[PDB]
Length: 307
Ligand SMILES: C[C@H](CCC(=O)NCC(=O)O)[C@H]1CC[C@H]2[C@@H]3[C@H](O)C[C@@H]4C[C@H](O)CC[C@]4(C)[C@H]3CC[C@]12C
Image (cartoon, rainbow, N blue to C red):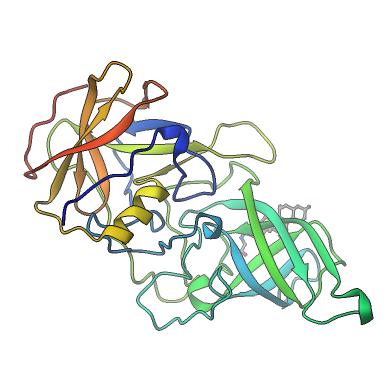
C-alpha cells in the first residue's frame, strides 16, 4: 500500500499542538533544547504517540468538572477533575502521559472556562456561565495524568461544582513559557510516562523543519509561537492510511505548482518529523500555493540539497 501525503498549502494546514492555522515554515538549530512534543506525534505508518489524538478542537482543551476550590486557597483557584476532552472517562492505566490533547508545554495558558449545569431550572433548562481562566501547566497541581488540574479565574464567586469546559485562547504571559519544556503530567509525584521520544537530526548539516503558528498573548510584550513537527492533517491522513514505511526516511519536495519547479527538499522521518539541509534560525520563505510532494523512499544517510 503506497504512502501518500495530502495535497495542502500551508494556508490549509492546522497546528497539531495548539488550535490555530499554520502561519509559516520555520527552522532552528535548537542547540541546548530537547525537542520532545507529545501532541502532534504520529509515525508515517499511522501510529499515534504521546498524547496525540485526531480532533483539532481537543488540542489544549479540557473537559470535566470543577469539584472544589483549591485546598488552602480561598480565592480565584479551582480544582478541576478532567476526563478525556471528548467526554469519555480517562483511564490512568493506559500508557499515555495525560488525557489525549492535554497541553505538552509549560505555560500559563489563557482561555475561557464555561459551565452548563447538569440539571434544569424548571422549564427554562440548565443555567450557564463562562469566565476568563488560566491553566498553569507549571503548577504543582497540574496533574492531568492523575485526572485533575488547577484552574484560575478572575471571577471569585460565579463558579459552581458543575460540568466545565476550558476553551484555550493563548498565553496569559510570557513568564515561564517554554514550548519545549514538558509539563510534569503527574505534578510532584513520580515522573512522566508513555512519552513519545525526542526527535533530532542525525545527519550533519541538517535541522528540523517546523510548522509554526503565532498564538495570542493576553498581556505584555512578545510574539510567542508554537512549532509542531507535523500538521494535524498529516496525522489524520497517516492514521487513516497506515501505509507501511518502506525505509526510515521519505524524501519530500516542496513544489511551486505555478512554475512546477522544486523549491527545496526534506527528509520525512519514520518517527514523524522533517529535517532539511539548512543552517540558521528563521522562517522558510515560500510561495502561497506551494505544497509538499512525496517522491521517494531513501536511507537515513541520504544527502539533501542545501537550501
Ligand atoms: C496558582 C497558579 C499557579 C502558581 C504557580 O505557578 N506555582 C505555584 C504552584 O505550584 O501551584 C496561578 C498562576 C497564574 C495565576 C492567575 C494569573 O496571575 C491571572 C489572575 C490574576 C488575578 O489577580 C488573580 C486571578 C488570576 C486568574 C491568577 C490565579 C492564580 C494563578 C492561576
